[PDB]
Length: 273
Length: 273
Ligand SMILES: [Cl-]
Ligand SMILES: [Cl-]
Ligand SMILES: [Cl-]
Ligand SMILES: [Cl-]
Ligand SMILES: [Cl-]
Ligand SMILES: [Cl-]
Ligand SMILES: [Cl-]
Ligand SMILES: [Cl-]
Ligand SMILES: [Cl-]
Ligand SMILES: [Cl-]
Image (cartoon, rainbow over all chains, first blue to last red; front, side, top):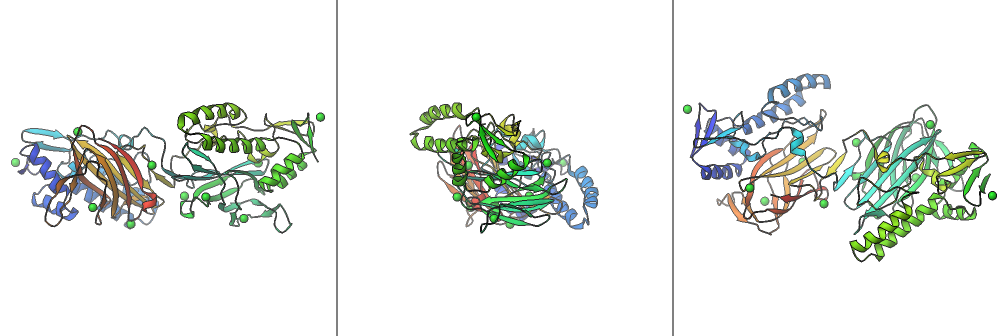
């Protein structure tokens, strides 16, 4: 038996067996079935609040005309849900509220204080102290990592058994590029030959164009001119004069992929030279 | 003019113009053309050493019968190249030596001490203090991150505009699962409905099988039995009784992907419950 006590503010189970059984039966239902089974019991659990919280976040993203308006709405939203729920302290672009619960499926029966009862025993369910405790791990290593536009002068894409990079530096107006590629073997990562592919869009820039039809290498103006680099097969450590600076600042973006790293998985970087 | 002095141990350029020109012309050549142009000058540069270092690492991976033998070979290799070159201090599976040079294309002309000359001026080229200084960045954010088998009880795949996760925890033998999914909007990440896909291979495990043909939910033995989970469309925060422990330890692996995150980009995790 499931009993709603303390004027619809507490779920009480007969014993451990009743609780574990109700958890299995309720967690196996569809969201609508769960919402209706809880409506049957006239009990608002943390799960019903999560439905509401998620519904309200989706509506805030739809009514907000601009960032400043969203910021006003979202501050009120966080204040509203930021006590029962927890927000992402690592990535501030992740807007969603989170359960504080370690034993996640208990969300169906815990109340607004994270409580439920087994007979005369009160269970204050196990919670995370902070969001960082939930995502905490001893590892630094990942299967895959691809750089975004917040990476400065360094673009990479490390996949499961192939890596590619484009590293930029500048000495007296001369821009140096390092094209890199590795393959995962039985003993680890080692350099291997590949074809490099880049998409360069830079301001105040001259490209060090390679020899073509017996003309060049020559500095070709690419000031705000997007262009592509599709090399021939080369080693895993290629060093090149990438170009020169025409102005005080050389800004823009770079994208890098290879024969082994597909365009979809290309690495990005903002250029500041 | 390019002049090899101090009995083939130093490259001397006439002026800055000669150096910048030779750097452009040499960096635009093919690897073989560069190796031959340097052989023409009877000068061994850091570039020729990198060719040798890379060639020797590839040969060590081919002659090593096992890890312990490689370890003996690779210790001697590191000692040999670990002064002129730099090894990866962050990822120990990355075996390759690295240039200490900031201005990478200078590898063609720098000697074994990272030197070259402009007339009577000696240039001790700019180097990185440590490997960490080369990979150093202020950002924590990436475009893409996928967990590997070193991630314990948490598998994820965060792509450019879609995320998926499978988080496991255990309370008194009852295993709790959290299936998560987010989409990137104009204001950031928010929850959205998707179809989840998992590949589970666990020891000492009973799966909490959902209702099928009016039978269950029921605990089905999956002790060392690989099996798949292909859900129907569900929200971005699904909580489930995943199963139960049959023994003292529940170990194995989990793989997670979704309708938005393709199988290729599926996240991994080792399970220890
Ligand atoms: Cl009452
Ligand atoms: Cl990006
Ligand atoms: Cl400069
Ligand atoms: Cl090209
Ligand atoms: Cl390849
Ligand atoms: Cl001499
Ligand atoms: Cl992996
Ligand atoms: Cl346990
Ligand atoms: Cl299934
Ligand atoms: Cl989708």
